[PDB]
Image (cartoon, coloured by chain):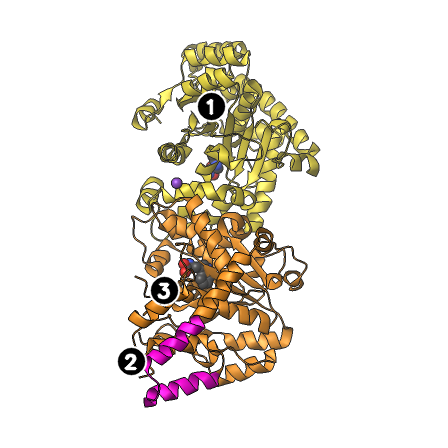
Chain colours: A orange, B yellow
Amino acid sequence: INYNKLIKEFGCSKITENHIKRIEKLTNSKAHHFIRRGIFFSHRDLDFLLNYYEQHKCFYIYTGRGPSSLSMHLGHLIPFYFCKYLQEAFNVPLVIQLSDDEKYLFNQNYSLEYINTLTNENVKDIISVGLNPELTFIFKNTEYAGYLYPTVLSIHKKTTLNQSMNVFGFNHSDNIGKISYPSFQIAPCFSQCFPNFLGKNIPCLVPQGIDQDPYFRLSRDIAVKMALHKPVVVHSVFMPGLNNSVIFLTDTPEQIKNKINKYAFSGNLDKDISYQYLRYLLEDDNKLNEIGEKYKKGEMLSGEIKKILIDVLTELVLKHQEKKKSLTDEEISYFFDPNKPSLQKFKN
Amino acid sequence: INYNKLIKEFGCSKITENHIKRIEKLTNSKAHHFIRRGIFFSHRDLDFLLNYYEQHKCFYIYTGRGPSSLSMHLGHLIPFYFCKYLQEAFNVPLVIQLSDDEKYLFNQNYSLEYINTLTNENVKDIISVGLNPELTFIFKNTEYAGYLYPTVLSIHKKTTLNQSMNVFGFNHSDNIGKISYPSFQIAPCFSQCFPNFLGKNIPCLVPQGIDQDPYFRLSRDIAVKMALHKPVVVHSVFMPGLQGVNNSVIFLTDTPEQIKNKINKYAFSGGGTTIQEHREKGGNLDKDISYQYLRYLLEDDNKLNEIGEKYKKGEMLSGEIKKILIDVLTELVLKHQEKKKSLTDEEISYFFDPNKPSLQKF
Ligand SMILES: N[C@@H](Cc1c[nH]c2ccccc12)C(=O)O
Ligand SMILES: N[C@@H](Cc1c[nH]c2ccccc12)C(=O)O
Ligand SMILES: [K+]
């Protein structure tokens, strides 16, 4: 996949060192390694957002999760780790949508109950990332649709069937729920969908996988029509693989060791899957650079990098499972309260 | 239109004398004149509904209004007079949807605010019909969508885009909100949409204009897929506007004067012809718009029969019938206006409360 080609093809902008310097200046801390290492690499209107934060110290983050399975892996958790950082760095509210409606509509043999099981577990996996419970609002569409609906209607009216089908690749055999859904994913980009804790027309930062862009490329056109702020968009590169070409957060140190040893492509910094995974997982640059140099020059063996990765991954997965098991129902239910005076309520 | 052709074409059935006698038996009161005179004439699954009421003494009514205008007229209020009757006769909950979302999505230049301004007035017109507040729940889709959504999702998933477009005549230029909407009108046909006061899979009676049938022809095929009851449906004929089958209709904002004008200058006369020719010809009830309206407004079958007989035989003048209509209309409209003016904000708010103990029957 040619990312630089995609940026210019769909009208995005590369994240620059200036963006980073301004982020560190405004947050009074070091930028996350996702930004420094170009994992989150492209954006729309980030400059506007940074200036708006500088001038008003106010905005909110919005991301989502589609509960189509019980088994999440690290790639799914990448944007949530990132939202955790943004949440703490700027001290702003985070909003997380669970498109249980989408997964119900797109999966023919799935019922709402099943989707809800998947949803609850995915929610616990997401919370287990380390999100600030005070600065977080999670919602299921099946429950928050009433708060989303007037905004959805405006988006509905400004989206022709032609546009929905062209943008999302729908055909005439798809159910009208699939056609109507994208407005519900677009809606939370507008702060009127959260009257309990947010003011009107507050800029929205949307961290997302690249594959989610069609939703928010459309949201920016409709935002102009609705006379509201265009969603500030931030994209991530797809996490590379190498049928269990992934690391599940239910996996054991044993299975992680086996998968890494037997399947992780080795390589060359750019073809070694393990060094990339370390690019994701290692916060300190010195380490990453040392391992990178030793490996590129030949001093370090493959099985070494494999070992260090297995260690890091093992600690991560174990801590995550611990946090997961630690979760009480009240702790989870707290995340669904929009009435927290707490952070949530200060952004007006 | 040929209604008997429609009945066969779309798989409905005429309401019979057996149905009327049975309704009178179960309600212990005379059947409403809308039924006796074939104004509400066609149905689906009325026998099942009457059996169910005989067995459990309960069901619920569902009808709706699209707030597309500030000025409602008689034809608009026809099914609401009919719902007031059913509500009182059977002693059952009445559910009323205001599809402000529909009218927002179908009218390019209407804001949600303007629409809301419309439905707030439409609601007062609807209530002023004489609905029982204790047995009535009114809701705006813009406010109740959260209660509708899980059911709408199931209906969505069971409707292909092709089917939606073919049933409702949509094209690829229509917004996706218009394609989405029908599931929201279909949703209240299922009691799970009213958890606060309704029980499990309760049979739903939907009185409607004949042009709403595609919604509920679709609701019945979808119920089968959701394993829920098919909506018991009851249709009314179109109320013939003035000037053949402002100002071919009479508004409930009109003054007695305006009604006088409208009738005397625009009511099709049927009998008419030459000043004397009518004395022996004489008067044709089927074409006389006045007698047709009196069919809607006169409860007493005997007055209607007398006026009609005299006007058909020729003794009655077009102007006389005209005048009878002026006074009936005037009384009705004035009464409606007084009732509408008397409405307090709290009385109105009481209609929107889903937690009324009077509604709470499981
Ligand atoms: N539909 C997305 C989940 C999602 C919903 N809202 C979002 C907003 C931003 C990013 C992702 C989302 C998926 O299945 O992957
Ligand atoms: N769509 C109808 C109003 C309506 C909504 N729900 C209904 C249920 C039954 C009959 C009519 C309705 C109209 O504009 O005329
Ligand atoms: K189902």
Cα separation, mark 2 vs mark 3, equals: 22 Å
Nearer the observer: mark 2 or 3; the answer is 3
In the foreground, A55 or B266: A55
Cα separation, mark 1 vs mark 3, equals: 84 Å
Q: Please state if A289 lies on the left or on the right of A192 as rendered.
A: left
User: Please, which chain is the residue tagged with disc 2 on?
Assistant: A
User: Please, which chain is the residue tagged with disc 1 on?
Assistant: B
> In the rendered image, which residue does mark 1 sit on?
B289
Secondary structure of the residue carrying tag 1 is helix
Asked whether residue A287 is drawn in magenta, I would say: yes
Screen quadrant of the N terminus of chain A = bottom left
Q: What residue type is labelled 1?
A: Ile
In the foreground, A67 or A71: A71
> In the rendered image, which residue does mark 2 sit on?
A267
Secondary structure of the residue carrying tag 3 is helix
Q: Is residue B11 shown above or below A218?
A: above
Along the polypeptide, which appears first: circle 2 or circle 3?
A: 3
- Picture quadrant of ligand 1: bottom left
Magenta-highlighted residues: A285-313
